[PDB]
Each structure stands twice: as structure tokens, then as C-alpha cells.
Amino acid sequence: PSVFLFPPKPKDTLMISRTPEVTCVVVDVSHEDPEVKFNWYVDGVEVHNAKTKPREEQYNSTYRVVSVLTVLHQDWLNGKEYKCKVSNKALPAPIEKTISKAKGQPREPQVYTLPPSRDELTKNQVSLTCLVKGFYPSDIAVEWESNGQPENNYKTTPPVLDSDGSFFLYSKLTVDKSRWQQGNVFSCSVMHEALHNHYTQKSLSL
Amino acid sequence: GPSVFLFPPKPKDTLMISRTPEVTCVVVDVSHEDPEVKFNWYVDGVEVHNAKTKPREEQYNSTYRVVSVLTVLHQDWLNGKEYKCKVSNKALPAPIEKTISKAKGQPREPQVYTLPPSRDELTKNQVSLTCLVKGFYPSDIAVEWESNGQPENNYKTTPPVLDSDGSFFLYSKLTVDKSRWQQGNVFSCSVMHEALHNHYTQKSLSL
Ligand SMILES: *[C@@H]1O[C@H](CO[C@@H]2O[C@@H](C)[C@@H](O)[C@@H](O)[C@@H]2O)[C@@H](O[C@@H]2O[C@H](CO)[C@@H](O[C@@H]3O[C@H](CO[C@H]4O[C@H](CO)[C@@H](O)[C@H](O)[C@@H]4O[C@@H]4O[C@H](CO)[C@@H](O)[C@H](O)[C@H]4NC(C)=O)[C@@H](O)[C@H](O[C@H]4O[C@H](CO)[C@@H](O)[C@H](O)[C@@H]4O[C@@H]4O[C@H](CO)[C@@H](O)[C@H](O)[C@H]4NC(C)=O)[C@@H]3O)[C@H](O)[C@H]2NC(C)=O)[C@H](O)[C@H]1NC(C)=O
Ligand SMILES: *[C@@H]1O[C@H](CO)[C@@H](O[C@@H]2O[C@H](CO)[C@@H](O[C@@H]3O[C@H](CO[C@H]4O[C@H](CO)[C@@H](O)[C@H](O)[C@@H]4O[C@@H]4O[C@H](CO)[C@@H](O)[C@H](O)[C@H]4NC(C)=O)[C@@H](O)[C@H](O[C@H]4O[C@H](CO)[C@@H](O)[C@H](O)[C@@H]4O[C@@H]4O[C@H](CO)[C@@H](O)[C@H](O)[C@H]4NC(C)=O)[C@@H]3O)[C@H](O)[C@H]2NC(C)=O)[C@H](O)[C@H]1NC(C)=O
């Protein structure tokens, strides 16, 4: 087999109402030795909370077996280490993989909305841009709204490392030019550990 | 045994006839016991004989790394020819074949828009000049900034991102001193992509 260990989604660790989890994915499980055991540890202290998902027979005739561990928001954000220890009869010895939050001082994102270029105003749809810079760690979530309703026609770049060791990204919301021209107000919502209440919003309208 | 990585040309290299685009087939984890490596190269399945293969080089981990480089014609790559590298070695149960080409699809022309700093950014020492490039296909592209003929050092560009209509977009962010912006220096975002006339377009930005 092989073992991959995955962090929680950024949004999930920032809101207590959400449920962040670490996920341990075991691939290339054969039919001849299908028995997978998981042990989990949080800073070396064994914990007992994880659930194994119903496996998927993969299209290469191997099993994908997945364990999910719920994490405390504040444990993840304070940098605790999550160790998944995997065993299987085709493995020489148990594989461990460990994960934790990027290390270092969190830095507050600066959020800037930018209207469409004049040149773009010739098209049927236009691009509303939210630049989010100066943040650390790169874990962040960005969404758009209007009139408190999610606007879902948007795409956000991955975080990119900037020259000062912080990250930036851009999010692009596309809207019908007629919605823009009629003065509708659009909001770029940013969630990040270094924002007050883990959230901020910036408006954009004509 | 050995593992093979096959690398495409850089996007600028296939777009400018002055440049030399190359496909590079790298074999690592070649052992001492079976160190001979043989490459065979194909273009659309037809064998070609003009690659340049370098002697094996031992790595610090006591395996060999062996590289073969095939020059490609600009128009072959841009017409979607498939380049196959086949690597034979006596430790393998069968030769390893790897293939690379430009992503399949009709090319699409990048639309290039420049956007000035947000009003709110103007209380900072440095401001952000943004170039939005969208609607392009395939995703191979190059973006640069300059002012007064000279390249601007401090910019970063996002990877291409797949858009909801199947084309790509990206943004590139040039950081300048607020004073330079304020004095009306003209900056220009230049873009190179196969679906642009002369594989180039440029858009300017100033206050
Ligand atoms: C023994 O040593 C050798 C040599 O290492 C050297 O010496 C040792 C002792 C140490 O000192 C090392 O620090 C030192 O470097 C080891 O050889 C390495 O082997 C690994 C695999 O085990 C290779 O990993 C691959 O790397 C490529 C990227 O490689 C480029 O970038 C590297 C730096 O980032 C650079 O080091 C490489 O030279 C190479 O650089 C490029 O070179 C090309 C050609 O010259 C040039 O044109 C470019 O300009 C230049 N670029 C840069 C940035 O410099 C990476 O792409 C591979 O990942 C793919 O495959 C993975 C599976 O193996 C997979 O998980 C990844 O997702 C990815 O998969 C690809 O995904 C995309 C979709 O996005 C898809 O399109 C692809 O199809 C898919 N590919 C596949 C195959 O599925 C991968 O990580 C190292 O390159 C190689 N090092 C060298 C120098 O050749 C060896 O491991 C050691 N052995 C042991 C037993 O220890
Ligand atoms: C049989 O069929 C199977 C399915 O097709 C196939 O299983 C596949 O196996 C490969 C390994 O062989 C495995 O590859 C890893 O993928 C990691 C990313 O996985 C993400 O994203 C992919 C899509 O990109 C999804 O398919 C995955 O499901 C997974 O999704 C994430 O999962 C959880 C859901 O629980 C979510 O929370 C996430 O939201 C979700 N993300 C996304 C985007 O969807 C990738 O990290 C791995 O890369 C690392 O390891 C490689 C070595 O194997 C390195 O080459 C690579 O460089 C990465 O290295 C790490 O990088 C760090 C620095 O960047 C280093 O510090 C680390 O040390 C370094 N690790 C190293 C060197 O070991 C890796 O590619 C696929 O995930 C898996 N597919 C599925 C569906 O599970 C089988 O192989 C098939 N078998 C055979 C024999 O043919």
C-alpha cells in the first residue's frame, strides 16, 4: 500500500459550528491482504476518535481505505501534530505519516476589490476581482455574495508565495454585465485565522 | 527499477522561432548491477534518431541518472505532435514508455485586462498592479511586466486556473513603490500565447 495524510479544510477550522478533520488515505490495498489497522496520536498522546469509511474498490483492482479523525479547532490552530500509524500484511513495517499546521506568526490578509477593466465592458459578462494579500499561513477561504445570497459563478487561484514570505491569491467572480451596470453590490468574503472573528468582507459596486 | 520523467518545452520556447524548444526524458534509479540505458524516441509513433543523450551520471545515492534531449520543431509542438520516450534497461520487466504533447483542444485567445490598485491600497508604501489574463487555451502561457523598456523585478503570477467554460485564467501582480505609481509611470503587462497574433500582446497601465 501507501499512506497519505491530509489536513482539514481551512474553513472548517475557523468556525466552531463546522467540524474540521484530518484524513488518512491508504491506497494500493490488495485483495490478498485487505486488513488495514489505523492508530492515531495527537502530540504522541493516543486518541481513540477516528472512523473508517466504507472502502472503494479502485479501478486498478486495489482498495482505497480512508480513516477520518475529528480535530479540535483550537488544537489544529495551535499547531498540534497528527500522526496516523497504518498496518497491513503486505507492509514490511507500519507506515507512519504526520501533519500539522504551517509554523510561524499568522499574518492578517489585506483584501482589495477591483472592478472590471474598461476594456472588459465591451463583453456580455465582466470580471469582479478580489485580491487577498499579505496572509500567513496559506490556509484561507474566499466566497462571494450579493444581497446576502451566495454568488457561485466564481473561481479562486491557489495561494501563491510572495516575495516577503506571505501569500496572496485572487478570486474572480463573473457576472452579467447588466447586473454590474445596474449598481448591484457584490461582496468578497475572506476567512483566515489572522482576521478578527476569522472573517472579513469587502464590497464592490459601480 | 528505474523511473522516467518526461519534461515539455517551456511555453516561450515553442512560441518564438529564435528559441530552441526541447523535450527532456530523464531516467533516475538506474542501478549499478544493470546500468545500460537505451532510449528510443517517437513523434506521432514514428521513430526519430536525432535526440542527444548524455552519458550516465552517478548520484550521491549510488544510482545513475541518464538524460536524453530531443529538439522539437515549434510548429510540430503547436500542431499537437506526440513525443514518446521509451527507456529500456535490463532491470525492467518491460521498457517504460512516456508520452507528452500540448494539451488537446482548440486554442483560445487570452483576453488581457489591466487593473489599477484599489483606492484602499493607496495608504500603503507599495501598491499592486494587476494583469488579468482569461479565456485562454491551452494553459501554456508566459506573462511579464516592464516599464520604460526594462523588466520589472518584483512580480508574481498565479498558476493557470481552469475556468467554468473550459478555458484558463490567471492573474499576475506587480508590486511597485506607491511614489512610482503616483508620478504616472506607465507599466505594461505582456503576454505570450499561441492564440495571440505574433504570439504576443501587451497592455499598459498608469495613473
Ligand atoms: C537518487 O538521487 C536522484 C537524483 O537526486 C539528486 O541527488 C540525490 C542524491 C539528492 O541529492 C537529491 O536532492 C538530488 O536532486 C533522485 O532523482 C529524483 O527522483 C525523483 C523521483 O523519486 C524525481 O521526482 C520527480 O520530480 C519531478 C520534477 O523534477 C524537476 O524539478 C526538480 C526540482 O523541483 C528537479 O530536481 C528535477 O531535476 C526536475 O527539474 C526539471 O528538469 C527538467 C528537465 O531537465 C527541466 O526541463 C525543468 O526546467 C526543470 N525544472 C525545475 C523546476 O528545475 C516531478 O515532476 C515529478 O512528479 C511527478 O511524478 C510523481 C510520481 O513520481 C507524482 O507524484 C507527481 O504528482 C508528479 O506526477 C505528475 O503530475 C502531473 C500532473 O500535474 C502529470 O502531468 C504527470 O504526468 C505526472 N507524472 C507521473 C510520472 O506520474 C517527481 O516528483 C526527481 O526529479 C529526481 N531528481 C532528479 C535531479 O532527476 C532519486 O529519487 C534518488 N533515488 C533514491 C532511491 O533515493
Ligand atoms: C489505483 O487507483 C488509485 C486512484 O486512482 C491510486 O491511488 C492514488 O495513489 C497515489 C499515489 O500513488 C496518490 O497520490 C498522492 O496524491 C496526493 C494528493 O491526493 C489528493 O488529491 C488527489 C487529486 O490530486 C485526489 O485524488 C486524492 O484523493 C487526494 O484528495 C484529497 O483527499 C482528501 C479527501 O479525504 C481531502 O481532504 C482533500 O481535499 C483532497 N484534495 C484534493 C485536491 O482533492 C499527493 O499529496 C501526493 O503527493 C505527494 O506524494 C508523492 C509521492 O507519492 C510525491 O511525488 C509528491 O511530490 C507529494 O509529495 C509530498 O509533498 C511534500 C512537499 O510538497 C513533501 O514534504 C512530502 O514529503 C511529499 N511526500 C512524499 C515525497 O512521499 C500523491 O501524489 C493518490 O492520492 C491516489 N488516489 C486516490 C483517489 O486516493 C493508485 O495508486 C492506483 N494504483 C496503481 C498501482 O496503479
Image: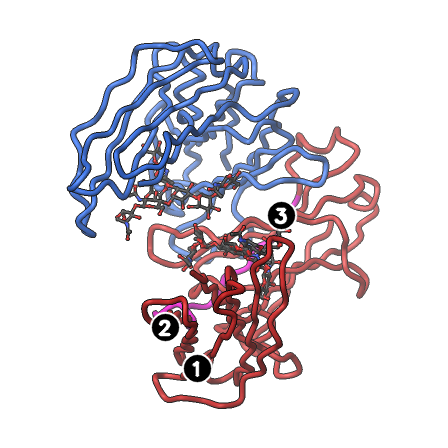
Chain colours: A blue, B red
Looking at the rendered structure, the number of numbered marks drawn on it comes to 3
Residue B40's disc is 1
Q: Is residue B4 left or right of residue B187?
A: left
Ligand 2, seen in the image, is in the quarter at: top left
Which chain letter matches label 1? B
Q: Residues within 10 Å of mark 2 (few under 14, many from 20)?
A: some
- How far is disc 2 from disc 1 in space, using C-alphas? 10 Å
Which residues lie in the magenta part? B101-116
Q: Residue at x 17, y 38 (%)?
A: A56
- Name the residue nearer the viewer: B180 or B2: B2
* Residue B12 locus on image (x, y percent): 60, 71
Measured along the vertical axis of the image, is residue B7 above or below residue A112? below
- Of the residues shown, which amino acid type is indicated by label 1? Asn
Residue B95's disc is 2
Which chain letter matches label 2? B
- How far is disc 3 from disc 2 in space, using C-alphas? 47 Å
